[PDB]
Image 1: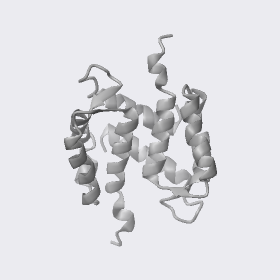
Image 2: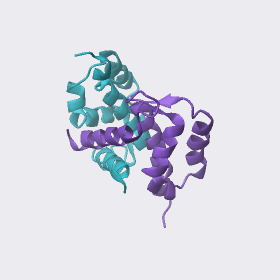
Image 3: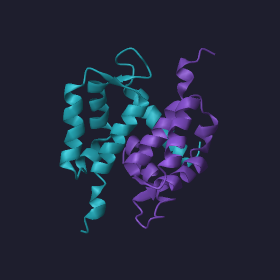
Length: 93
Length: 93
């Protein structure tokens, strides 16, 4: 819709590109989410700054991987990785 | 960067469009965030389905409004409203 809403409707397309592994099309298993995060959010992983926070999400899901997530969860985790790569705001190169 | 990452970099731009009331531009006060959500997330607000959930965020922030958020928080709340307007998944039209 608006620029913000088209940004979010993009997150839906991307979530749905990997969703359905489990059988539910609006859900994605947590271990399968790590694949999406490693594939599309790969550039933010390469640009990570908070090595603590990036791994705090990954290792946490690595053991909880056999669970699942929906769009809301997926975006929360995406945003968390995004700020772990944005913390450079306080680094005056 | 990627399709997902440009989706998220859009969320940064549009967060920044109303940010800096407190002077920090990577932050926005919570009551001031409601404005952004009412302006840009207005279409998702119009398309709301989970009336309980949409208000759970708004009424909550209306009393917690004098605090503040960053990109991570703002995106979580945006995603929460997004799923409250996506609920048609459980509506057999």
